[PDB]
């Protein structure tokens, strides 16, 4: 699972 560019916008 290399999908950390979809949750980063929120985790940022």
Image: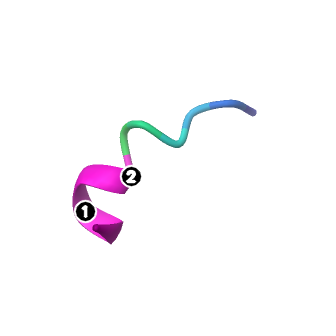
In this rendering, the answer to whether 4 lies above or below 10 is: above
Helix, strand or loop under label 2: loop
Magenta span contains residue 10: yes
| Dot 1 crowding, Cα within 10 Å, few <14, some 14–19, many 20+ | few
Residue position for label 1: 10
Mark pair 1, 2: CA separation: 5 Å
Q: Which mark is residue 7?
A: 2
Tell me which secondary structure the magenta stretch mostly adopts.
helix
The answer to which quarter of the image holds residue 10 is bottom left
Left or right of residue 8, residue 12 in this image:
left
Of 12 and 10, nearer the camera is 12
> In percent of the image, x 34 and y 69: which residue is there?
11
Magenta segment range?
7-12
Up/down of 10 relative to 5, above or below: below
The residue at the far right in this view is 1
**As drawn, is 2 to the left or to the right of 3?**
right
Query: Residue 8 appears at what percent x and percent y?
Result: 37, 53
Per the image, label 1 sits on a secondary structure element best described as helix
Q: How is the image coloured?
A: rainbow
Mark 1 in CB contact with mark 2 (< 8 angstroms): yes
Which quadrant is the C terminus positioned in?
A: bottom left
């Amino acid at each position: 699972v290399f999908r950390l560019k979809k949750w980063i916008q929120k985790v940022i």
